[PDB]
Image 1 (cartoon, rainbow over the protein chains, first blue to last red):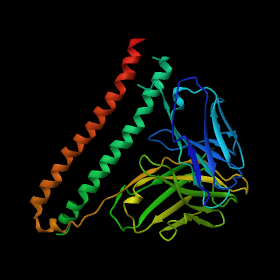
Image 2 (cartoon, chains in turn orange, blue):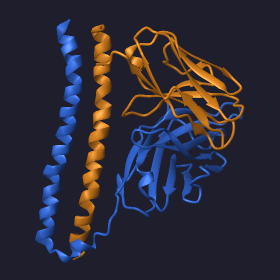
Image 3 (cartoon, rainbow over the protein chains, first blue to last red):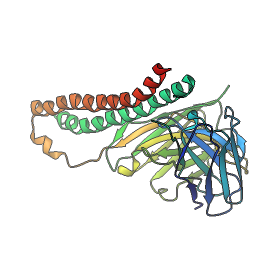
Image 4 (cartoon, rainbow over the protein chains, first blue to last red):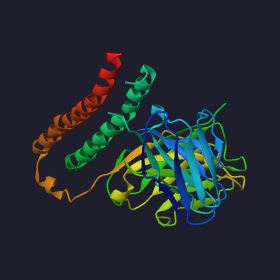
Length: 152
Length: 174
């Protein structure tokens, strides 16, 4: 019913460069919520009640908005931040999510070793997700033959 | 102390079948007013699509687009919440999370998320042809899938090694 619109759909930034992303809605929205999700894992509550940071969210993040103008602002982008951010509302049924902004690093393909290590780890959950979907492809592929055998 | 959620899925289904999901949780009860748990699903490489919800007072909410298919259930003593989806097709292949929302009347948001479960809708052709084959002929094709599967998996491994290599070379350099 209320449709959340996220722009930009994809955002490419440089480490240390302030950015801002927006979510706009058909109708007036009492509160805007934000969720971060790195590929392969569950989403994390990032910003709630339009401008409140969840436990463990870096101070470099910020939320702002009123009416149907809602925006997230990263003060100083860092490599760990690269993820898809979704906006969500519950002003009325049904609750709805935005398209999400995928945050990417300009230079993704010589920082501090901590940063390089962080990006190095982010890779593992994607690969597991991909591998698993290959297992269910063959779990699906396998099932017809089993049933035919299981007949008698 | 804190809240966890765990979703129990079936892995794979064929079309038209009733997909059923379990979500077990700890750290809160659905005997506490304001407590509620909703189902959200995410297609691979696509966005979040909220599904259903349920409250302490047994009050349900549904995606209007799919409500006829959906049904949401709860087990207050057992701390379980069930989502049943009927007559499934390819559009149901997704990763199904399970989340909590506290209803105060003001902000209603999802404060804790389970790990999620991944379901695949077997794109299902007529497979009556097999029933012509005997056991041993069927065993052959069954045996063929395992080497074929592990080759697509090592391909995903090699693909991510080539992604690791620029960062790895960045580490050893300095």
